[PDB]
Amino acid sequence: KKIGLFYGTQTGKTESVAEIIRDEFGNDVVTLHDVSQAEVTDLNDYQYLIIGCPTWNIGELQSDWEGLYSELDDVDFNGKLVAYFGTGDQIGYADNFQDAIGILEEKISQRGGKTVGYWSTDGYDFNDSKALRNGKFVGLALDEDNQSDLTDDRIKSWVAQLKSEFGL
């Protein structure tokens, strides 16, 4: 009803985590939007947003999201609070781990969005990332290929953090 969660997914992991995030928030607070069936103008309807996008393209963005990216200039995000999460492989993409959410954040904050939900890089083994803001990632970094046993606990901690930041 109040937080719009827009995700794009390739193998379905970002979508399953989006449903978990939805449940952790509860009370009909978050409405899920698969970006394959969304329009950029749908983002304008929320004052609270959660952007989900995996990184599997070594120097490109998830197809569904790749499309919306070009039209992100058509939307004013000033006043909106935005959080980010994505899936990736810190070993197979050591130099580009979670690049997708960093690209998205750069664009959105330029348009006026305020990033909420920074997440610690501790416990990850990678080299670089466009999502790296230096001591923290721009949002929740998940790795189901190497750290699937840490996923639910990470989601649990991040949602508790977002509850405070979003004022829930």
Image: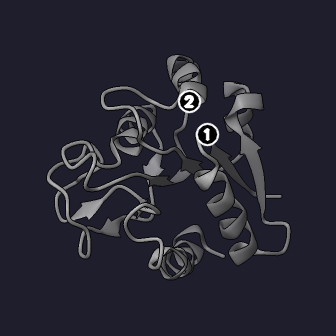
Q: Nearer the viewer, residue 77 or 36?
A: 36
Q: In this view, does 166 lie to the left or right of 16?
A: left
What separation in Å lies between label 1 and label 2 (alpha carbons)? 6 Å
Is residue 138 depicted above or below 113 in this figure?
below
Dot 1 or dot 2, earlier in sequence: 1
Q: Is residue 138 left or right of residue 128?
A: right
Give the number of the disc on residue 65. 2
Residue 158 visible in the current orientation: yes
Residue appearing at x 48%, y 45% in the figure: 54
Q: Is mark 2 on a helix, strand or loop?
A: helix
Is residue 74 depicted above or below 125 in this figure?
above
Q: Which amino acid does label 1 sit on?
A: Gly
Pinpoint residue 117: horizontal percent, then vertical percent.
Answer: 44, 65
Query: Looking at the figure, which quarter contains the C terminus?
Result: bottom right
Residue appearing at x 39%, y 32% in the figure: 57
For label 1, the crowd category at 10 Å Cα-Cα, with few meaning under 14, some 14 to 19 and many 20 or more, is: many
Q: Do the residues labelled 1 and 2 touch (CB within 8 Å)?
A: yes
Is residue 112 depicted above or below 118 in this figure?
above
Residue appearing at x 25%, y 55% in the figure: 91
Pinpoint residue 74: horizontal percent, then vertical percent.
Answer: 58, 19
Q: What element carries label 1?
A: loop
For label 1, the residue is 8
Residue 49 visible in the current orientation: no
